[PDB]
Every structure is written in C-alpha cells, then in structure tokens.
Image (tube, grey):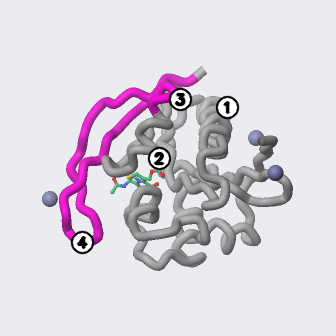
Amino acid sequence: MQLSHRPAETGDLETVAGFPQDRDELFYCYPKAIWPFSVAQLAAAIAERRGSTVAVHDGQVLGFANFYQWQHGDFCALGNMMVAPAARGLGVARYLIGVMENLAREQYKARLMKISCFNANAAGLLLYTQLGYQPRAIAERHDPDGRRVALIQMDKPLE
Ligand SMILES: [Zn+2]
Ligand SMILES: [Zn+2]
Ligand SMILES: [Zn+2]
C-alpha cells in the first residue's frame, strides 16, 4: 500500500469532505462541525489550523489531518483525522500520523504529540495505542444530542 503526502489544496476539499460517513464519524474527527459536513466547514478548519496534509495512493486522496494546537518547542495536537471509506484499515491513518509526527518535530520542534479521542471510537483508541500513545486524562464533553461523552486525552513523546 504505497502512500505519499503533500499539503492539502483547494481541489482536495470536496473529496475530503466526503470522508465522514455519518454523524458519529464527523463528531469523532471534528466535534465542532454540524452534520451534514461541507467544504465550507472543512475550509474553515483549515484556515484556523496548521499543517493540513493529505495522503495519496494511486492518484487518490485517501487521508487528511492537521494540527488544532501547536506550541513551538513543546507539542502539537492532531485533529481532523479522516480516511476515505473505501480505504479504512489499510494503514492510511498510521501513515499520516507518522507524517504529522515528523512535521511536529521538524517544523514545530515539538517534544510531544497530543491526540484526543472520543470514547466511542474504539478503532481510534486502538490505533493510537498501537502507535505508542498513552492515555493521560479523561474529559467530559457533550455530543450533538446533548449526551455526555468521554474524551480520552492521549500523548506520545516524539523522536
Ligand atoms: Zn513531508
Ligand atoms: Zn492501489
Ligand atoms: Zn456537561
């Protein structure tokens, strides 16, 4: 499964905004967004974040991520981790997270990556655990129906 990466471009937005397949998936990767997702909502996140990057395989954009927090010499916080529905479980998020870790180290001199994952997203919790992230705290948040959820705040030292 050969993959490459590059900064996200305007032309990618419609593709990436196609990735979340339901309100749960949108909530897990962008909890401030409102279903249905849209290019305007994706562009607004890009404009206020840093490091928006796509993963590409065989001419297809298959993954997207960015940083929603960045503190030079300190840490970055990874967000908006989205994978194309036809490419789930094939290593795209693993790949892109590694790219983003290098970007945090190289550009931001980060010592730490933070990832926060909602409790219902088992696939995410297990992936981040496989990649060496450890849970540090649990924060209460609310979902779009007003129901209480647990945000599991994880981190990993970089090198
Ligand atoms: Zn690169
Ligand atoms: Zn292929
Ligand atoms: Zn509350």
The mark found on residue 131 in the picture is 3
Say whether residue 116 is magenta.
no
Q: Which residue is mark 4?
A: 145
Residue 18 vertical position relative to residue 154 in the rendered view, above or below: below
The amino acid at mark 4 is Asp
Q: Give whichever of discs 2 and 4 has the lower sequence position.
A: 2
> Is disc 4 in contact with disc 3, using a CB cutoff of under 8 Å?
no
Residue 31 sits in quarter: bottom left
Q: Secondary structure at mark 4?
A: loop
Give the magenta-colored segment's residue range.
129-158
- Of labels 1 and 3, the one closer to you: 3
Q: Give whichever of discs 1 and 2 has the lower sequence position.
A: 2
Q: Which residue is mark 1?
A: 106
Q: Give whichever of discs 1 and 3 has the lower sequence position.
A: 1
Residue 21 vertical position relative to residue 139 in the rendered view, above or below: below
Q: CA distance from mark 4 to mark 3?
A: 31 Å
Q: Which residue is mark 2?
A: 69
Q: Position of residue 84 (x, y in %)?
A: 63, 60
The amino acid at mark 2 is Gln
Disc 4 residue crowd, few under 14, some 14–19, many 20+, Cα 10 Å: few
Q: Is residue 151 left or right of residue 55?
A: left
Q: CA distance from mark 2 to mark 4?
A: 26 Å
Q: Position of residue 59 (x, y in %)?
A: 84, 58
